[PDB]
Length: 49
Length: 48
Image 1: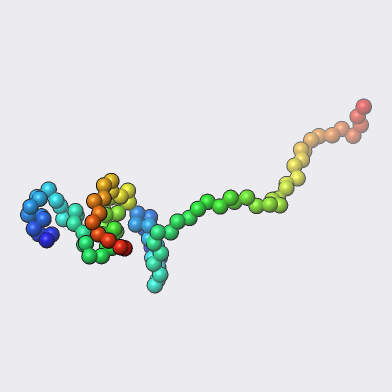
Image 2 (image 1 turned 120 degrees about the horizontal axis):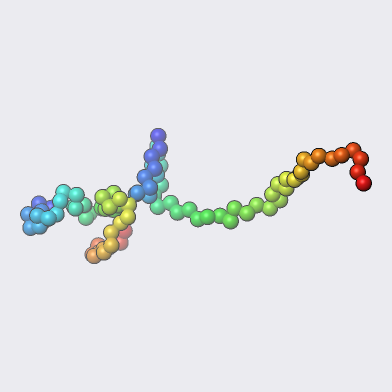
């Protein structure tokens, strides 16, 4: 069982006891991100001029 | 000492005292202040 106390900045579970954990934002920038194919569903007459 | 201080200063409540011989006072202060902490800290202890 785990308990997190943001007020005391302590996380306790089992036989472990973490205090004063500090986390810093990562850039979160990943290369080669997915590139979706964008299209429009449009009517099209068979014959045009 | 706690009893003597309580006698000297009636304003002090049972929640305004901690233990000076260990680092347990930190949790007490943080809890009773809602995690905000204190403003002035007249520190006289040492090391940890």
